Image (cartoon, rainbow, N blue to C red; front, side, top):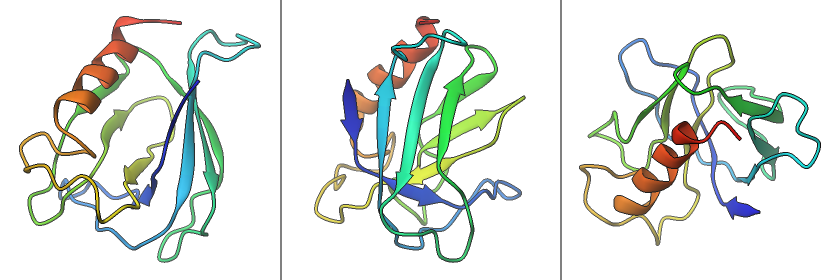
Length: 127
């Protein structure tokens, strides 16, 4: 399975912005070796607690065509994961590493092309 490092970023999208407040965590991108619902679970874990928000651990199904991928929604901020979630909870993430994701802000999430390709592949799959 594919593991990636990020903490959370606020629930907020009432101005299409959420601010980084530093935190850590871990996402596990997996097909689910139980396949109960038959979708991708992003298992978030706190490794630092959310401060200035409370978002609990979550096993998060991405349901194609209900989950929309936008690669960046902030220009006063960098490294924002933007997933519009309908029929599910909304979790926005911010990469915990200030040394990486220094690639320019036009697609920035943690990288440009890699995250963009990867996130489109989850929509294409229903696995």
